[PDB]
Each structure stands twice: as C-alpha cells, then as structure tokens.
Length: 257
Ligand SMILES: [Zn+2]
Image (cartoon, rainbow, N blue to C red; front, side):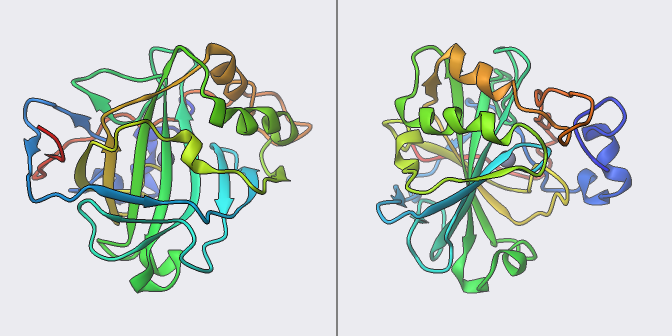
C-alpha cells in the first residue's frame, strides 16, 4: 500500500488513485506575487472555545488528534466558506531536517512542517459524504518554522512516546487547538484536494501566511515516531509530505494586501 518511500511514495500514487494527476490537486506552490488580493474575502471565523479532543492515533503515515464532531463544538466559517465546517482532526507533515517538510510552499520556500486542521461541511451530515463533494472540506494549513518552542504544542509532543508505532492510540482529552494558531489569520485560499490517498478533490484550502515557531526539540520528537507497526523493523516517520502539484486552471486568492 501507499506511503512515502522510494517504492510507494507520491510518484507511485497515481497507479491506485488516478486522480493524483487531476485538475485540482494539492499541495501547490503559493507564488505570492501572482496571488490576487480579493477584498470580497471575509475574515476567517475560528470558533474552537468548545472543542472536545478525544484521542491521538498513529495511523502509519502521521498522527491524528481526533475531535468529537457529533455537534457544532469546534467550527470554521467565514473566509471563503459558505456555511459551517466542523473540526474532525488535525495532523502534521514534517521532514527529516528543518529545510523540508511542508506540503505547500511559499515562493518555493519549504517550511520544517505543516499543520492541517481538517473540517467538514455540515450540509453533508458526515465526513464520508463530505469528501464526495467539491465544497465538502475546509483544511486550515499552518506552517511551522524551527526557533522558539510553541507552548501549546508540548502536550502533543509529550504523548508521542505512547503512540510510537502504526495502530497505537492514546486518550487525548482536553487539548485546546487554539494553542497551535499564529497571531494573524491572514490567509491564501484555493480549491484543491486531500494531499494523501484517496486524493479526493473536495477541499477549500485556507493557508495562513504567518507560520508558528516550534523548537528543534519539539520537531525532533516528531521524527522519533515510526511508520512501521510494533515488533517490525524501525522506519522513522519523516518526510511524510507530498510535493507541490501543478496549479493548472486555478487562482490563489489573498485575504490581505
Ligand atoms: Zn495533511
């Protein structure tokens, strides 16, 4: 099955998921000079005050922090979006070294990592139905650079020893995802896809301009995770990012001048 190796990585995905070569694939390079300021775009509304985290899972490609999405507790609205999108999970993509790891790039700059907060449109009732629709998901992408520690990330870092290998999960209640946001909600937006199989073209991407800073020790703990299951040969979970895909007939819009 698919992964990030020489034999099963992004350039192989098209064989099982032909949409890999589709017209609205993610991620993309954000050319900051070509992105158009769109004064009609609304400020993002991030309403995470009542978020209920439940669990953290090593799924063999990343780790997911899962939320209760059975009510409107943690929602994204406004920005480019029509209606209400419920937070279901967040995860990261990161590198083997600090010079790579993000999926989106900015003028070809690669960040050390990228956080994806995944939300689904409540008009489709469940995540599985939402991924079948062109406006089904809104993913909030946040870049990570290495410098100062991010205090709000440390609870995540400290549980990773308990989910080292594929299929391990741990209770992860009372985590506040507000602690992962930068100060500014200035963003770019474009229509795209899931960045892992099944690569469905169901995402409104919202990529924040302002990165968050994490410490070298925090990202080093990400890199101690394993792709493999328990009692299998150790394969470090690093470089779990898809490279930039062709922009094709798309416009990236900026919320800011
Ligand atoms: Zn992702």
